[PDB]
Image (cartoon, rainbow, N blue to C red; front, side):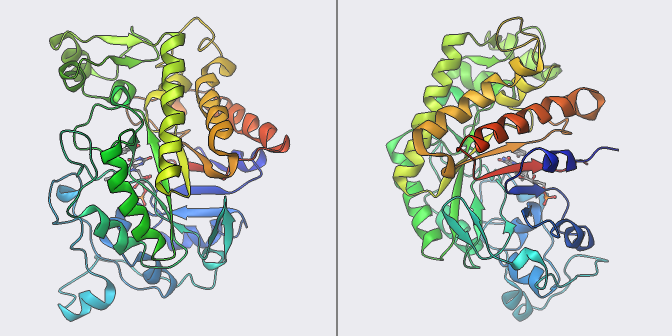
Length: 383
Ligand SMILES: Cc1cc2nc3c(=O)[nH]c(=O)nc-3n(C[C@H](O)[C@H](O)[C@H](O)COP(=O)(O)O)c2cc1C
Ligand SMILES: O=Cc1ccc(O)cc1
């Protein structure tokens, strides 16, 4: 037992929800009755570039391939057929033992304004790491990336949240994930954003910082710290081992280094806007750096950034306030995963985990009531 419904009693703005919604249209039908609820479809947007149409008319869906999720290939990336295409090649089978359902009559296809963007429907593309950025440089794929996003900007007025983008090398750790700090990166993102906009759709860049989820050896190779909230608690056995082997132990961030991250958040945010992005999403979920500060298991600090609910939320909120001041509140979003245990988070097992995120939602609303409301709040559903 555990629901994200508590957020609605606190935060009074747009809410994006994602997690196992594609194969459960009866759940979606109930949830979208709330006039400010949007739905994110992850794995099946990968397999269905025309997913928005298949949801409106209740069409069968293509199966997805887990093996080609993070593979450096066009296969399982840009070679997923639309429904009109899949028919011409046969069928011959789609998703097995599934009864589709038309949702074109529900609020899922009623327009709504998110930030500056006039969405025509509420089926959102959540951030989806595909690990196809070029190494070295963390550069967006020059061969397939533009076509990949183009296929999924198919339906006009579609909100798209990009794969997690590193705000800086220090925030990185994955060689095949795109960054958002350098020029040659922005040259590629500019093409991507243009292709999206030419399909009358919108694109939001997720600002990503790994934390203890980063590969310690990759950071040691580049003379970078393997940092997190604390230094006495680790993600798992492998990560602690790889940290000692590369002689790059887990580093507890100092206040100055925290300020440095914020500065990198700002620069990355302005880089995205300058490149022509509609807005940015602050990734504060799924066990990465900001979540590592939020979660009491990963945060054993005794200073201003730990020891309490208010302190553990300071980093996230400071990043929010910084980006709001930098590019405006109408271009800033925030993703949370209250019940998530991914990357060694506490989840519902921590009895005070709801209070922790209730506080964050409250602080967002206080800023909203004071005249600075974020574009949306992105929530990862319990599982
Ligand atoms: C291959 C893959 C990559 C993902 N990458 C990200 C990511 O980079 N950032 C993020 O916030 N969520 C990421 N997610 C989680 C999705 O945003 C979404 O929550 C997840 O797909 C569950 O929704 P679903 O049931 O529709 O698949 C990823 C999920 C998958 C399957
Ligand atoms: O941010 C969450 C996330 C989940 C799975 C991934 O592969 C990458 C990121």
